[PDB]
Amino acid sequence: GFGCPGNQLKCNNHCKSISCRAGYCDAATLWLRCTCTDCNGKK
């Protein structure tokens, strides 16, 4: 991911730093990855 496990805010900040709104750690992967959800960069 990019912070997890034990770093869900790091994914949001990382998603906000990259170009998104807020992400989350694959809750289906025991929270490890750092996915990005909702982004403001389309058309």
Image (tube, helix red, strand yellow):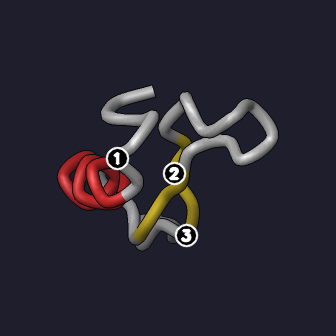
Quadrant where the image shows the N terminus: top left
Q: Which label sits on residue 7?
A: 1
Residue at label 3?
A: 38
- CA gap, disc 1 and disc 2: 13 Å
Quadrant of res 8: bottom left
- CA gap, disc 3 and disc 2: 7 Å
Residue type, mark 3 in image: Asp
Residue type, mark 1 in image: Asn
Q: Secondary structure at mark 3?
A: loop
| Residues at discs 1 and 2 in contact (Cβ within 8 Å) | no
Q: Which label sits on residue 36?
A: 2
Residue shown at the point (26%, 47%) measured from the top left: 14
Left or right position of 27 against 40: right
Quadrant of res 9: bottom left
Density class for disc 3 (Cα within 10 Å; few <14, some 14-19, many ≥20) is few
Left or right position of 40 against 24: left
Earlier sequence position, callout 1 versus callout 3: 1
Residue type, mark 2 in image: Cys
Residue shown at the point (51%, 51%) measured from the top left: 36
- CA gap, disc 1 and disc 3: 18 Å
Earlier sequence position, callout 1 versus callout 2: 1
* Residue 6 point in image, percent of width and height: 39, 43
Density class for disc 1 (Cα within 10 Å; few <14, some 14-19, many ≥20) is some
* Residue 4 point in image, percent of width and height: 41, 35
Q: Secondary structure at mark 1?
A: loop
Residue shown at the point (23%, 57%) measured from the top left: 13
Residue 28 higher or lower than 16, as above or below: above
Hey, which residue is sitting farthest left in the picture? 17
* Residue 7 point in image, percent of width and height: 34, 47
